[PDB]
């Protein structure tokens, strides 16, 4: 009569919630490992304002015919 | 054991009361290793400071409330009492026993009681009964082993498949359950192996 | 596999070890303390040329030979090559137990080096990062780094072998009364 | 007494990410193997009784029970859930 | 009310007790018995009809690092007990107060540090049985080595420096390969938890690699031949509490580690590798027993004796048989009872009286020390596996399992029954036998304290030997959870 | 703030006496604390790993570099506290530890060079900053000019750093000769797999790495660390390493190099073995730093190494500061002052410290077992994350070497603890002089961090996943 253990159903449910939290942390770790080592933009990786990688060089003797696409 | 049995003055006197005595290690020996070398007034003196070791000079509500300067006094002049007591107890093989009416205590022989160790009340009244409780709990949790459950379940499955056993007499159903168990297969393990059936 | 040319690789081995021994002898001659000259590079070198050449010849010869005898390319060949190189390095100390210990221990060490891939570097297309990982999706063959909830039983029986509990059919279904 | 009778779950019908059903299936497998063992022990007890009652007639009277016990002993025993949990016999 | 109020009450009481009486051993023994009682209450409130993990709690979560988690994303350390955990937890809480009381009167310099280290090691071992992931298990499996180093170095015998360095370095050597294994598991599965790790089936060629590291750790911790040489030195040159704790619990952590880390995961690698385990175990049995037959130090003899019984336990746990698992667990428990009693006799009774452990000095204790002789005979015949002691039950069932798995090796391993008797009774016969030694003066017989400890440890093993079945209500799932048979 | 500090302190020190340098150090320590408190909200710029290019395209600012800068400020705070606060107000400790007039200015200029190394995006900035670090740290080694050993170390360090700077400049100008550029942003997949470029890049890496003691070029820096003052050694053994390794980790230059693997294995073996027969404390700690530099070399071969490097460098910095502070605290109990500059040299002078100060030995034990990598301490999680990365990237032999080095180094780490917990005759019973409050608090805080920082690992990972991924 002194034995008052938590029932089997509630034990199973609590363990299941724990395992669900653990699998959620697993999937979050995988997602974060995948969002890292994913190619980012030039604005996010180098320069958010001057977002043009194309260099405009000197200006003192700028020859027409020097630009090229 | 008492609640509030601390009294500053006797400790603050007892400090140099004990400092006037020789060291505990060298008192009862005299450097000649003989109880006889110590004088007999000195011996009674040592006896009545040593009997003060096993006296309630502090309570719970005095250790929880008073300050450090008094507790340190108690501690460092209780260590001396302890060491005097036990060095006499070993060298002389006598404990001090103040008898009832005469107010004079001296080392005596009687060691068939009136002495208890400090670990006994902890163990014999917190540890031993807890292990007895563990034995009780183990014995009565053994009733919940799966063997008994499986026996009851198998009998119940047989009774569900063959309800005709119940109207038979009450001291004959066991043999009939045994007969039907021996005949049939009331387990449901191949029931659970669904993908093994090709 | 494709066989190794033992004598050619071992001749290259010997020339490389000889050059390395010359370089080490020159370095020792220039770093040393006492009076020294261009004479002492080979007089006072502590067998550096013979160390390098012997180790090189022994390692490459034993490696290619074991690869051609065993008819395989694996780390045991590096175990044998390390055994031989250690035997050479231990014959210098003119004692038997030191020779045996050198042989056995450098064999074990180089065999570990070969077991792990025979490289201080990484493969970098067999690593876990660059390889398909995680749970495999639909009945596909489980690769090395992939994970599976439930494996095939034919695969288990082949990898492990029948007996000692592991059988081609479960016991309960195999002993089920045909009813 | 409130004797419990839990529901039987199989590994073949569940999704292994629902851990409750996986534990139900483990416990189901183990419980049914214990029921198999109790059947084996019933057979053994009957064999013992027939031996103790018959004596020299046990060779004839207890024959089927003895053969049944030795047929059941290798197979009606505890053999664990992992072997079926981690292996699909259909492949 | 508050949590902090209650533990601050306990902390203030501890501080005042230390201020007034300058010692901690009474408070630590009170906490010892209180923890034992709390664990018994948890056993009262434990459901035997669920294989699940109970009394779960999570620590060091992102949302509540200094508290318990209720999150839907679990990133901290997981804790919780199964029946297997609870068995060894009962053993641990039974033994801790006895290890404190075994050194009650023989530590007269920096006592409080000794008792702190002892209780700390015990609580680390308890929490290690409470663990439910590879990383919490590891950080509680390796956290004892600093404490053991300090304890053995400061409070140890003549050769204590060597023993301190051994108990750290050997164990760290094995445990770092265990760490490589755990790291591989975590990067491959992205999860570390003992609840659903039998659902993840790795490839065989990777199981066979993870198993190597875990088994090197188990070989250094069990111990097993050829890496068993640290155990005599450490168990010999340590203080009594250290030897008791070590032989009783830290050696059993390896058995628990097999059952909890290596069998549920890595089932196919185990079922391929176990003949190598049987090689190593049979060697560990016979050669260690024979090596015991030529030792001159008593505590060293008992130390060597632990290794053979742990090898029999390894035969049992690596048998793929329910009876073998149950036998290995009963061996662990009964050895954890009996071996600290022998260590008490040879390191706290005799060593406290004579401060020497060489067998040539000891002879004829029966004349002046008869109660001690009775205890020696009882504990010897219990250690060698006499029936009606749990040692026999465990040995019997472990060898049953070993015979079922490999009849030849499991049958050859039954000379354990003989060699145990040889190396134990060759010592008992000399100690109890003959005329009392001329190198030893007379001293007191065993005290009430020593007798209390030995009597607890004898009652326990006799209970579990006369009715081993009382341990089944916490193990009838565990004896089938780690069996790989199709 | 650093340049403001430099331009302020130059004037204020020129117009001040030598009696005021300690208070000047206190002032600038509080300045750095206020900066690290009030200006540290700039972490919000780097949300979702937003990266910024500043001063044209000469500097780069991301979460990595912001973190390394906060770390360098924390280190400078501790090192300045050791100079601005007297341990004991005795004549001895006013003879041993006195700041020189220009020392704080040189420290701040070296910190400037450190940060302009980690923030560099173009090789001209890198070279200017490398030289601003190395000249200042020559002069820091030389400022205690009344020491023969320190002058000698100054000159050795000048010449060896000069040669390695020649190597760096050759690498840079060869890169320019090939690609006509000074920027590593100019590289991509195509340029790497189209041009063979590994000689130049590994020449740069080695010119930077041999400046922090990478084998076989370790003996000179170990001699410099031995022969310098203790309170100079504590700085010159740590901050250059942080700077250069952080640059080499941010710049993905040696992703699968065989040479760097070989030299890292060599660093591990040397840093573990050579420290076994060392009888002196600073050489032992130098070989410890060498093997930790090897552990951090290993993650120059990964391409995803931010978390491991930041964790390990933070914990190594805390442990390094703590152990040097414990050796500085132990001078009150050693029985023989060796020099005015290195008052404690040999490890056996720590014999019996547990009987004079037991909790100092508890601190030593915590730090020693963090160096060994014992859980639940911080070095264990460091080693764990490094192992995770290198095994995820396929370095399986290096891992076993790492374990073996972790084991061999424990012996000389435990030498200290072993001799410290030994017994000694002539113990301390009373002393009316008390050690400083501030330095005691700093050491206790470092020890508590080592001991209880594992509680926050979940939180740190969750923050990393937002600011670095
Ligand atoms: C993981 C899971 C682990 C599971 C663990 C299992 C649970 C563990 C349980 C531990 C129990 C501990 C109890 C305890 O703490 O007691 C402390 C306490 C410690 O002993 P102590 O006497 O105080 O020691 C100090 C000396 O006495 C002081 O010195 P001394 O002067 O007194 O010297 C005397 C000493 C010295 O003599 C010697 O040297 C001889 C060596 C001692 C050997 C003792 C071993 C026991 C022998 C039993 C013999 C039976 C054979 C059959 O000899 C003895 O004390 C032995 C007395 C022999 C019995 C007397 C005859 C009365 C009848 O023991 C007791 O008070 C009595 C405990 C007895 C309980 C036994 C259980 C019997 C159960 C009844 C059977 C039928 C029903 C069973 C079903 C139950 C359903 C509920
Ligand atoms: C001429 C014709 C050429 C033909 C073309 C082919 C030639 C191939 C040449 C290969 C290179 C050979 C170089 C030989 C090494 C340099 C000589 C040397 O002695 O190195 C050690 C040097 C001096 O040592 P010493 O003064 O003699 O005293 C020794 C007492 N202990 O002192 C030093 O510190 C210098 C060290 C230089 C080391 C370079 C890096 C070596 C990397 C070590 C590999 C470790 C990897 C193994 C990992 C296993 C892990 C268990
Ligand atoms: C894991 C981290 C490793 C920690 C291992 C413990 C190392 C402790 C070594 C130093 C020590 O003795 O701890 C200090 C102890 C007090 O030492 P104590 O014997 O009481 O001497 C008088 C104190 N004023 O104070 C203590 O009680 C601390 C106990 C830990
Ligand atoms: C430290 C001393 C802790 C003693 C244990 C206290 C305790 O267990 O109280 C449990 C209390 C009541 O729980 P209970 O009776 O079991 O009923 C559950 C129904 N809700 O419920 C509670 O108080 C909440 C649960 C308490 C969890 C205790 C966690 C102790 C962990 C100590 C961390 C040690 C740090 C060292 C590093 C560890 C690294 C692994
Ligand atoms: C600073 C002081 C001032 C003096 C400076 C002196 C001039 C500087 C010389 C160059 C710069 C020094 C470089 C330092 C040595 C380390 C270079 C290095 O490690 O780069 C090697 C690198 C490949 O290594 P890695 O990228 O790590 O691995 C992947 C392999 N696919 O890249 C490579 O693959 C290298 C390409 C291989 C060719 C090497 C050329 C050597 C040719 C010598 C032949 C001599 C003739 C034979 C012997 C004559 C002796 C008599
Ligand atoms: C930063 C001062 C460093 C000085 C040394 C003191 C350590 C401070 C750690 C805080 C780091 C953080 O909270 O940040 C997490 C960082 C990135 O986050 P962040 O971009 O820098 O934003 C932080 C914004 N602050 C500045 C306002 C806080 O991830 C990491 O890899 C940190 C790895 C370090 C692990 C060491 C843990 C030490 C235990 C800490 C116990 C309180
Ligand atoms: C000091 C104690 C030392 C004892 C510890 C021993 C642990 C050493 C690690 C052993 C496991 C290494 O694992 C090993 O497995 C696979 C085979 O399964 C090898 O197999 C691989 O080898 C390499 C080299 O040719 C190629 O990728 C090849 O195609 C194959 O895939 C790997 O080269 C190695 O990674
Ligand atoms: C002490 C224990 C810890 C040791 C430390 C190292 C742990 C990691 C073990 C090494 C992993 C080696 O793994 C490596 O070899 C296996 C083969 O076995 C290869 O696996 C690949 O093998 C090829 C055959 O060559 C097959 O197509 C197979 O399907 C798979 O794709 C991978 O290229 C790589 O995964
Ligand atoms: C360092 C000394 C070593 C000590 C080792 C012994 C530790 C023993 C701890 C065992 C007690 C764990 O008991 C545990 O029970 C439940 C799990 O269902 C936890 O979780 C409980 O949290 C509370 C939240 O308010 C709610 O009741 C919730 O429904 C849940 O039941 C408790 O927070 C914890 O108390």
Image: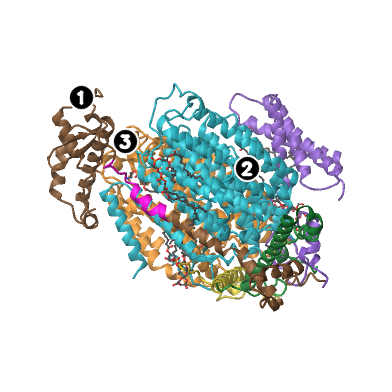
Q: How far apart are marks 2 and 3 (CA)?
A: 44 Å
Asked if labels 1 and 3 share a chain, the reply is no
Chain in yellow on the image:
A
Chain letter of mark 3 equals F
Q: What's drawn in magenta, residue-wise?
A: B113-129
Cβ–Cβ below 8 Å for labels 1 and 3? no
The residue that disc 1 covers is: B36
The residue that disc 2 covers is: E224
The hue of chain C in the figure is: purple
Chain letter of mark 2 equals E
Q: How packed is label 2: few (under 14 Cα within 10 Å), some, or many (20 or more)?
A: many
Label 1 element class: loop
Q: Is residue F104 visible?
A: no
Q: Nearer the viewer, residue E153 or F228?
A: E153
Where, by quadrant of the figure, is residue F53 drawn? bottom right
Q: Is residue E68 visible?
A: yes
Q: How packed is label 3: few (under 14 Cα within 10 Å), some, or many (20 or more)?
A: some
The residue that disc 3 covers is: F427
Chain in brown on the image:
B
Q: Residue at x 55, y 34 (%)?
A: E301
Where, by quadrant of the figure, is residue E239 drawn? top left
Which quadrant is home to the C terminus of chain B? bottom right
Asked if labels 2 and 1 share a chain, the reply is no
Chain letter of mark 1 equals B
The hue of chain E in the figure is: cyan
Chain in orange on the image:
F
Label 2 element class: loop
Q: Which residue is drawn at 42% across and 50% down?
A: E119
Inspect the magenta stretch and tell me whether residue B169 lies in it: no
């Amino acid at each position: 009569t002194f034995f008052h253990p938590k029932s089997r159903e509630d034990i199973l449910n609590e363990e299941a919630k724990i395992v669900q939290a653990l699998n959620n942390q697993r999937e979050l770790t995988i997602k974060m490992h995948e969002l890292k080592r994913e190619e980012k933009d030039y604005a996010h990786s180098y320069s958010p304002l001057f977002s043009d990688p194309v260099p405009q060089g000197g200006s003192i003797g700028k020859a027409p015919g020097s630009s090229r696409e | 054991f008492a609640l509030r049995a601390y009294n500053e003055e006797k400790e603050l006197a007892l400090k140099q009361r004990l400092s006037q005595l020789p060291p505990p290690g060298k008192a009862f020996v005299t450097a000649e290793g003989e109880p006889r070398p110590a004088k007999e007034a000195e011996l009674a003196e040592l006896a009545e400071i040593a009997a003060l070791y096993k006296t309630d000079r502090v309570g719970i509500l005095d250790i929880l409330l008073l300050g450090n300067k008094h507790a340190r006094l108690y501690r460092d002049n209780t260590a001396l009492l302890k060491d005097y007591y036990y060095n006499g107890r070993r060298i002389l093989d006598k404990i001090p026993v103040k008898d009832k009416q005469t107010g004079k205590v001296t080392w005596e022989i009687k060691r068939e009681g009136a002495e208890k160790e400090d670990w006994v009340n902890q163990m014999y009244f917190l540890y031993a009964p807890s292990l007895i409780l563990l034995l009780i709990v183990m014995v009565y949790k053994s009733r919940e082993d799966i063997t008994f459950w499986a026996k009851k379940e198998l009998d119940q499955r047989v009774l569900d498949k063959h309800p005709e056993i119940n109207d038979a007499p009450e001291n004959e159903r066991d043999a009939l359950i045994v007969e039907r168990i021996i005949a049939g297969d009331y387990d449901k393990l191949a029931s659970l192996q669904k993908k093994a059936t090709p | 596999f494709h066989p190794y040319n033992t004598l050619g690789l071992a001749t290259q081995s010997a020339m490389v070890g000889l050059g390395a021994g010359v370089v080490a002898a020159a370095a020792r001659n220039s770093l040393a303390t006492g009076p020294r000259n261009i004479l002492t590079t080979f007089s006072k070198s502590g067998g550096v040329v013979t160390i390098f050449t012997g180790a090189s010849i022994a390692y490459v010869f034993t490696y290619c030979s074991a690869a051609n005898l065993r008819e395989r390319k694996d780390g045991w060949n590096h175990m044998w090559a390390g055994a031989a190189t250690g035997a050479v390095l231990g014959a210098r100390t003119k004692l038997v137990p030191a020779f045996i210990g050198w042989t056995v221990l450098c064999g074990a060490a180089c065999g570990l080096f070969g077991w792990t891939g025979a490289r201080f570097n990484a493969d970098r297309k067999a690593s876990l990062e660059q390889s398909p990982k995680g749970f495999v999706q639909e009945d596909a063959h489980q690769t090395f780094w992939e994970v599976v909830h439930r494996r095939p039983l034919s695969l288990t029986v082949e990898q492990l072998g029948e007996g000692r509990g592991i059988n081609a059919v479960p016991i309960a279904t195999a002993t089920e009364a045909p009813n | 007494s409130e004797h419990q009778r839990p529901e039987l779950v199989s590994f073949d019908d569940i999704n292994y990410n629902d851990h409750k059903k996986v534990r139900e299936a483990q416990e189901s497998y183990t419980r049914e193997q214990f029921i198999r063992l109790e059947a084996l022990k019933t057979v053994r007890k009957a064999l013992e009784k027939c031996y103790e009652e018959s004596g020299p007639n046990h060779f004839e009277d207890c024959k089927n029970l003895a053969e049944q016990y030795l047929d059941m002993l290798p197979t009606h025993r505890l053999q664990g859930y992992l072997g079926y949990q981690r292996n699909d016999p259909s492949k | 009310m508050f949590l902090t109020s209650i533990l601050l009450s306990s902390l203030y009481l501890f501080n005042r007790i230390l201020a007034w009486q300058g010692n901690v051993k009474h408070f630590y023994l009170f906490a010892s018995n209180l923890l034992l009682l709390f664990i018994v209450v948890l056993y009262i409130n434990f459901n035997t009809f669920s294989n699940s993990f109970q009394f779960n709690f999570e620590l060091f979560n992102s949302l509540n690092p200094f508290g318990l988690s209720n999150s839907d994303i679990s990133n901290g350390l997981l804790f919780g007990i199964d029946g297997l955990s609870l068995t060894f937890i009962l053993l641990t809480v039974l033994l801790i107060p006895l290890t404190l009381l075994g050194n009650w009167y023989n530590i007269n310099f920096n006592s409080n540090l000794y008792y702190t280290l002892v209780l700390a090691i015990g609580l680390v071992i308890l929490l290690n049985f409470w663990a439910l992931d590879y990383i919490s298990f590891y950080i509680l499996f390796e956290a004892t080595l600093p404490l053991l180093f300090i304890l053995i170095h400061i409070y140890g015998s003549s050769d204590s420096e060597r023993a301190s360095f051994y108990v750290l370095m050997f164990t760290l050597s094995g445990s770092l390969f265990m760490l490589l294994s755990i790291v591989v598991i975590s990067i491959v599965l992205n999860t570390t938890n003992f609840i659903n790790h039998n659902l993840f089936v790795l490839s065989l060629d990777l199981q066979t690699i993870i198993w190597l590291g875990l088994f090197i750790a188990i070989m250094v911790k069990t111990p097993l031949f050829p890496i068993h040489v640290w155990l005599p030195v450490v168990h010999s040159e340590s203080p009594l509490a250290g030897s008791m704790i070590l032989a009783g619990l830290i050696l059993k952590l390896a058995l628990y580690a097999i059952l909890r880390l290596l069998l549920p995961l890595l089932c196919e690698a185990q079922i391929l590798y176990t003949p190598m385990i049987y090689i190593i175990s049979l060697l560990t049995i016979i050669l260690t027993s024979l090596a015991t037959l030529r030792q001159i130090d008593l505590k060293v003899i008992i130390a060597y004796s632990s290794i053979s019984h742990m090898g029999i336990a390894i035969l049992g746990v690596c048998s793929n048989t329910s009876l073998g698992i149950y036998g290995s667990i009963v061996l662990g428990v009964a050895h954890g009872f009996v071996s600290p009693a022998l260590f008490l006799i040879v390191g706290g009774i005799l060593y406290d009286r004579y401060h020497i452990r060489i067998v040539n000095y000891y002879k004829g204790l029966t004349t002046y020390m008869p109660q001690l002789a009775t205890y020696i005979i009882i504990l010897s015949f219990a250690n060698i596996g006499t029936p009606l002691t749990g040692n026999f039950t465990g040995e019997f069932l472990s060898l049953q399992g070993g015979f079922i798995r490999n009849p030849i090796i499991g049958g050859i391993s039954c000379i354990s029954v003989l060699l145990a008797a040889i190396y134990q009774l060759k010592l008992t016969n000399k100690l109890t036998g003959g005329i009392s030694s001329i190198y030893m003066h007379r001293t007191n017989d065993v005290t009430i304290r020593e007798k209390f400890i030995m009597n607890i440890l004898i009652i326990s093993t006799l209970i579990i030997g006369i009715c081993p079945q009382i341990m089944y209500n916490l193990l009838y799932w565990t004896v089938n959870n780690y069996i790989y048979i199709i | 703030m650093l340049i403001l500090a430099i331009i302020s302190l130059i004037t204020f020190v020129s117009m001040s006496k030598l009696s005021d340098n300690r208070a000047i150090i206190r002032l600038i320590n509080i300045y750095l604390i206020l900066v690290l408190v009030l200006d540290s909200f700039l972490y919000l710029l780097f949300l979702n790993n937003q990266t910024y290019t500043v001063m044209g395209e000469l500097l780069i600012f991301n979460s990595f570099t912001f973190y390394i800068d906060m770390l360098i400020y924390f280190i400078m705070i501790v090192i300045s506290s050791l100079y601005g606060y007297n341990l004991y107000n005795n004549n001895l400790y006013k003879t041993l530890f006195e700041p020189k007039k220009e020392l704080i200015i040189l420290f701040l200029i070296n910190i400037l060079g450190a940060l302009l190394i980690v923030h560099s995006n173009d090789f001209i900035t890198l070279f200017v900053a490398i030289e601003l670090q190395s000249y200042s740290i020559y002069l820091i080694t030389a400022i205690y000019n009344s020491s023969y050993k320190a002058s000698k170390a100054s000159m050795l360090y000048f010449f060896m750093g000069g040669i390695l700077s020649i190597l760096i400049a050759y690498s840079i100008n060869t890169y320019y000769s090939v690609l006509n550029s000074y920027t590593l942003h100019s590289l991509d997949s195509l340029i790497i797999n189209t041009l063979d470029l590994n000689l130049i890049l590994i020449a740069l890496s080695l010119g930077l790495l041999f400046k922090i003691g990478i084998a076989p070029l370790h003996k000179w820096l170990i001699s410099i660390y031995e022969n310098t003052p203790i309170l100079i050694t504590i700085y010159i053994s740590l901050i250059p390493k942080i700077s250069i390794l952080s640059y080499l980790v941010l710049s993905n230059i040696s992703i699968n190099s065989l040479v760097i693997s070989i030299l890292a294995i060599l660093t591990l073996l040397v840093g573990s073995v050579g420290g076994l027969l060392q009888i002196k404390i600073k050489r032992l700690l130098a070989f410890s730093g060498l093997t930790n530099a090897g552990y951090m070399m290993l993650l120059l071969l990964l391409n995803n190494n931010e978390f491991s490097y930041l964790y390990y460098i933070t914990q190594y910095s805390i442990s390094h500061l703590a152990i040097f502070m414990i050796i500085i605290f132990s001078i009150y109990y050693i029985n023989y002052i060796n020099n005015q500059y290195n008052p404690i040299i040999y490890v056996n002078q720590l014999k019996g410290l547990i009987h004079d100060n037991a909790y100092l030995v508890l601190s030593m034990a915590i730090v020693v077992f963090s160096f060994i990598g014992i859980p639940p301490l911080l070095g264990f999680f460091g080693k764990l994350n490094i192992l995770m990365s290198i095994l995820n990237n396929g370095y399986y032999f290096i891992s076993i070497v790492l374990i073996v080095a972790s084991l061999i180094s424990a012996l000389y780490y435990l030498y200290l603890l072993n001799v410290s917990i030994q017994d000694k005759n002539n113990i301390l019973i009373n002393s009316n002089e008390t050690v400083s409050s501030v330095l005691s608090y700093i050491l206790s805080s470092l020890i508590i961090l080592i001991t209880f920082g594992f509680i926050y690992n979940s939180l740190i990972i969750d923050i990393f996943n937002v600011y670095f991924n």
